[PDB]
Image (cartoon, rainbow, N blue to C red):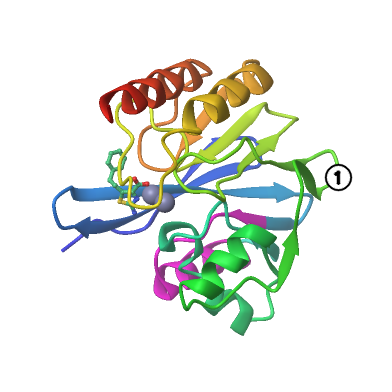
Amino acid sequence: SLPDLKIEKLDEGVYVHTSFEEVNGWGVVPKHGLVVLVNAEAYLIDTPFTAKDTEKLVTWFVERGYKIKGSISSHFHSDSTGGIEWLNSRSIPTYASELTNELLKKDGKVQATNSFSGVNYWLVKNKIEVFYPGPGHTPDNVVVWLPERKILFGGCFIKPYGLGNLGDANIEAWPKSAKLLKSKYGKAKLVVPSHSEVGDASLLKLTLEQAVKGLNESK
Ligand SMILES: Nc1nc(C(=O)O)c(CCc2ccccc2)s1
Ligand SMILES: [Zn+2]
Ligand SMILES: [Zn+2]
Protein backbone atom coordinates (compact mmCIF):
# COMPACT_ATOMS: atom_id res chain seq x y z
CA SER A 1 0.00 0.00 0.00
CA LEU A 2 2.61 2.55 1.16
CA PRO A 3 5.67 3.57 -0.87
CA ASP A 4 8.82 1.60 -0.13
CA LEU A 5 11.82 2.56 1.91
CA LYS A 6 13.90 4.98 -0.15
CA ILE A 7 17.66 5.53 0.09
CA GLU A 8 19.14 8.49 -1.77
CA LYS A 9 22.55 10.16 -1.72
CA LEU A 10 22.34 13.65 -0.21
CA ASP A 11 26.02 14.62 -0.22
CA GLU A 12 29.38 12.90 -0.09
CA GLY A 13 29.12 10.14 2.47
CA VAL A 14 25.61 11.27 3.48
CA TYR A 15 22.43 9.41 2.55
CA VAL A 16 18.80 10.15 3.38
CA HIS A 17 16.59 7.22 4.26
CA THR A 18 12.86 7.79 3.90
CA SER A 19 10.24 5.40 5.24
CA PHE A 20 6.47 5.84 5.24
CA GLU A 21 3.45 5.31 7.41
CA GLU A 22 -0.24 6.08 6.92
CA VAL A 23 -1.43 7.98 9.98
CA ASN A 24 -5.12 8.48 10.64
CA GLY A 25 -5.90 12.14 10.11
CA TRP A 26 -2.64 13.18 8.40
CA GLY A 27 -2.47 10.88 5.39
CA VAL A 28 0.83 9.44 4.16
CA VAL A 29 3.69 10.69 6.32
CA PRO A 30 7.28 10.43 5.08
CA LYS A 31 10.00 10.07 7.72
CA HIS A 32 13.59 11.09 6.92
CA GLY A 33 16.71 9.88 8.67
CA LEU A 34 20.35 9.80 7.64
CA VAL A 35 23.10 7.33 7.06
CA VAL A 36 26.56 8.84 7.53
CA LEU A 37 29.65 7.08 6.17
CA VAL A 38 32.92 7.52 8.04
CA ASN A 39 35.67 5.64 6.17
CA ALA A 40 34.21 2.11 5.76
CA GLU A 41 31.68 2.44 8.61
CA ALA A 42 28.06 3.58 8.57
CA TYR A 43 26.09 5.36 11.27
CA LEU A 44 22.30 5.58 11.32
CA ILE A 45 20.75 8.93 12.26
CA ASP A 46 17.32 7.81 13.36
CA THR A 47 15.78 4.43 12.56
CA PRO A 48 12.82 3.78 10.30
CA PHE A 49 9.49 3.01 11.90
CA THR A 50 9.85 -0.76 11.75
CA ALA A 51 12.28 -3.58 12.23
CA LYS A 52 11.60 -4.68 8.66
CA ASP A 53 12.58 -1.32 7.22
CA THR A 54 15.59 -1.10 9.53
CA GLU A 55 16.80 -4.50 8.31
CA LYS A 56 16.42 -3.38 4.70
CA LEU A 57 18.32 -0.18 5.49
CA VAL A 58 21.22 -1.89 7.23
CA THR A 59 21.58 -4.58 4.59
CA TRP A 60 21.62 -2.01 1.77
CA PHE A 61 24.90 -0.68 3.23
CA VAL A 62 26.34 -3.99 4.45
CA GLU A 63 25.95 -5.32 0.88
CA ARG A 64 28.00 -2.30 -0.19
CA GLY A 65 30.85 -3.05 2.20
CA TYR A 66 30.02 -0.80 5.14
CA LYS A 67 29.93 -2.06 8.68
CA ILE A 68 27.12 -0.56 10.77
CA LYS A 69 28.89 0.89 13.81
CA GLY A 70 25.85 2.43 15.49
CA SER A 71 22.62 4.37 15.41
CA ILE A 72 21.48 7.46 17.21
CA SER A 73 17.82 8.24 17.84
CA SER A 74 16.95 11.96 17.85
CA HIS A 75 13.91 11.49 20.19
CA PHE A 76 11.74 8.77 21.73
CA HIS A 77 8.86 8.51 19.23
CA SER A 78 8.73 5.41 17.11
CA ASP A 79 9.62 7.27 13.90
CA SER A 80 13.07 7.75 15.46
CA THR A 81 13.35 4.58 17.56
CA GLY A 82 11.27 1.87 15.87
CA GLY A 83 14.40 0.05 14.78
CA ILE A 84 16.31 -0.03 18.05
CA GLU A 85 14.94 -3.43 19.07
CA TRP A 86 16.14 -5.01 15.82
CA LEU A 87 19.52 -3.24 15.95
CA ASN A 88 20.13 -4.39 19.52
CA SER A 89 19.27 -7.89 18.35
CA ARG A 90 22.07 -7.64 15.80
CA SER A 91 24.58 -6.32 18.35
CA ILE A 92 24.65 -2.99 16.50
CA PRO A 93 25.21 -0.33 19.20
CA THR A 94 22.25 2.00 19.68
CA TYR A 95 22.53 5.48 21.20
CA ALA A 96 19.98 7.80 22.72
CA SER A 97 20.12 10.57 25.28
CA GLU A 98 19.45 9.60 28.90
CA LEU A 99 16.25 11.58 28.68
CA THR A 100 15.11 9.69 25.57
CA ASN A 101 15.79 6.30 27.16
CA GLU A 102 13.83 7.29 30.26
CA LEU A 103 10.94 8.27 28.01
CA LEU A 104 11.22 4.96 26.17
CA LYS A 105 11.23 3.08 29.49
CA LYS A 106 8.19 5.00 30.68
CA ASP A 107 6.44 4.38 27.33
CA GLY A 108 7.06 0.66 27.82
CA LYS A 109 9.60 0.52 24.98
CA VAL A 110 12.97 -1.11 24.59
CA GLN A 111 15.78 1.38 25.18
CA ALA A 112 19.00 2.11 23.38
CA THR A 113 22.02 0.27 24.82
CA ASN A 114 24.15 3.42 25.08
CA SER A 115 23.07 6.74 26.56
CA PHE A 116 24.64 10.18 26.68
CA SER A 117 23.69 13.40 28.42
CA GLY A 118 24.41 17.09 28.05
CA VAL A 119 24.14 19.90 25.56
CA ASN A 120 26.83 18.66 23.16
CA TYR A 121 27.84 15.04 22.58
CA TRP A 122 30.27 13.63 19.99
CA LEU A 123 28.99 10.40 18.53
CA VAL A 124 32.15 10.52 16.40
CA LYS A 125 34.64 13.18 17.38
CA ASN A 126 34.67 16.07 14.88
CA LYS A 127 32.33 14.28 12.50
CA ILE A 128 28.93 13.54 14.10
CA GLU A 129 27.71 15.87 16.83
CA VAL A 130 24.49 15.78 18.85
CA PHE A 131 23.01 19.00 20.22
CA TYR A 132 20.13 19.54 22.64
CA PRO A 133 18.38 22.85 21.86
CA GLY A 134 15.74 22.52 24.52
CA PRO A 135 12.28 21.03 24.46
CA GLY A 136 9.91 21.55 21.57
CA HIS A 137 8.34 18.74 19.56
CA THR A 138 9.15 16.54 22.58
CA PRO A 139 11.06 17.15 25.80
CA ASP A 140 14.00 15.09 24.56
CA ASN A 141 14.49 16.18 21.00
CA VAL A 142 18.06 16.45 19.84
CA VAL A 143 19.56 17.39 16.50
CA VAL A 144 22.62 15.97 14.75
CA TRP A 145 25.35 18.12 13.16
CA LEU A 146 27.80 16.95 10.45
CA PRO A 147 30.65 19.53 10.38
CA GLU A 148 32.37 18.52 7.13
CA ARG A 149 29.37 19.06 4.81
CA LYS A 150 27.53 21.40 7.20
CA ILE A 151 24.42 19.22 7.34
CA LEU A 152 21.93 19.57 10.21
CA PHE A 153 19.52 16.74 10.92
CA GLY A 154 16.68 18.36 12.83
CA GLY A 155 14.37 15.40 13.30
CA CYS A 156 10.81 16.16 14.26
CA PHE A 157 11.89 19.47 15.80
CA ILE A 158 12.35 21.17 12.43
CA LYS A 159 8.77 21.90 11.40
CA PRO A 160 8.86 24.67 8.83
CA TYR A 161 5.17 24.68 7.75
CA GLY A 162 3.26 23.42 10.81
CA LEU A 163 4.20 21.79 14.08
CA GLY A 164 2.61 18.41 13.59
CA ASN A 165 1.59 16.19 16.47
CA LEU A 166 1.60 18.26 19.66
CA GLY A 167 0.70 15.35 21.92
CA ASP A 168 4.12 15.33 23.59
CA ALA A 169 5.17 18.87 22.69
CA ASN A 170 6.13 21.78 24.97
CA ILE A 171 4.93 24.76 22.99
CA GLU A 172 5.97 27.19 25.72
CA ALA A 173 9.66 26.26 25.29
CA TRP A 174 9.69 25.64 21.55
CA PRO A 175 10.37 29.25 20.41
CA LYS A 176 13.34 29.60 22.79
CA SER A 177 14.71 26.19 21.68
CA ALA A 178 14.19 27.13 18.00
CA LYS A 179 15.80 30.56 18.43
CA LEU A 180 18.75 28.83 20.06
CA LEU A 181 18.98 26.32 17.19
CA LYS A 182 18.83 29.11 14.59
CA SER A 183 21.68 31.07 16.13
CA LYS A 184 23.94 28.05 16.56
CA TYR A 185 23.29 26.50 13.12
CA GLY A 186 22.64 29.39 10.73
CA LYS A 187 25.72 28.40 8.73
CA ALA A 188 24.20 25.01 7.88
CA LYS A 189 24.26 24.36 4.15
CA LEU A 190 21.51 21.67 4.45
CA VAL A 191 18.81 21.13 7.09
CA VAL A 192 17.00 17.78 7.05
CA PRO A 193 13.59 17.69 8.75
CA SER A 194 11.90 14.47 9.76
CA HIS A 195 8.76 15.01 7.67
CA SER A 196 9.41 17.65 5.03
CA GLU A 197 11.93 18.06 2.23
CA VAL A 198 15.56 19.03 2.75
CA GLY A 199 16.08 22.76 2.65
CA ASP A 200 18.70 25.27 3.67
CA ALA A 201 19.22 27.24 6.86
CA SER A 202 15.98 29.17 6.28
CA LEU A 203 14.16 26.09 7.62
CA LEU A 204 15.47 27.16 11.02
CA LYS A 205 13.79 30.55 10.67
CA LEU A 206 10.53 28.95 9.43
CA THR A 207 10.57 26.59 12.41
CA LEU A 208 10.96 29.51 14.83
CA GLU A 209 8.04 31.25 13.17
CA GLN A 210 5.88 28.13 13.44
CA ALA A 211 6.83 27.78 17.10
CA VAL A 212 5.97 31.37 18.00
CA LYS A 213 2.71 31.15 16.04
CA GLY A 214 1.83 27.91 17.82
CA LEU A 215 2.51 29.52 21.18
CA ASN A 216 0.35 32.52 20.27
CA GLU A 217 -2.47 30.32 18.92
CA SER A 218 -2.69 28.41 22.15
CA LYS A 219 -4.03 31.62 23.84
N1 LIG B 1 5.39 9.91 12.75
C1 LIG B 1 4.85 11.23 12.82
N2 LIG B 1 5.42 12.27 13.40
C2 LIG B 1 4.71 13.41 13.38
C3 LIG B 1 5.32 14.66 13.97
O1 LIG B 1 4.63 15.68 14.19
O2 LIG B 1 6.56 14.66 14.21
C4 LIG B 1 3.46 13.32 12.73
C5 LIG B 1 2.38 14.36 12.45
C6 LIG B 1 2.26 14.60 10.93
C7 LIG B 1 2.89 15.92 10.53
C8 LIG B 1 4.25 15.99 10.29
C9 LIG B 1 4.86 17.22 9.95
C10 LIG B 1 4.10 18.37 9.85
C11 LIG B 1 2.73 18.30 10.08
C12 LIG B 1 2.13 17.08 10.43
S1 LIG B 1 3.34 11.71 12.24
ZN1 LIG C 1 8.03 12.80 17.26
ZN1 LIG D 1 7.62 12.72 13.75
Q: x%, y% of residue 107?
A: 46, 72
Q: Which residue is mark 1?
A: 125
Check residue 45 for magenta coloring. yes
Q: Residue at x 36, y 27 (%)?
A: 215
User: Which residue appears farthest toward the front when viewing the image?
Assistant: 219
Q: Residue at x 70, y 74 (%)?
A: 113
User: Which residue appears farthest toward the right when viewing the image?
Assistant: 125
User: Which residue appears farthest toward the bottom when viewing the image?
Assistant: 89
93 relative to 205 in the view: left or right: right
Quarter of the image with the N terminus is: bottom left
134 relative to 197 in the view: left or right: right
Read off the magenta span.
43-62
Quarter of the image with the C terminus is: top left
Q: x%, y% of residue 143?
A: 60, 40
Q: Residue at x 78, y 40 (%)?
A: 127
Q: Is residue 83 visible?
A: yes
Check residue 186 for magenta coloring. no
Quarter of the image for residue 151 reads: top right
How many numbered callouts?
1
- Amino acid carrying label 1: it is Lys
Q: Residue at x 32, y 28 (%)?
A: 214
Quarter of the image for residue 189 reads: top right
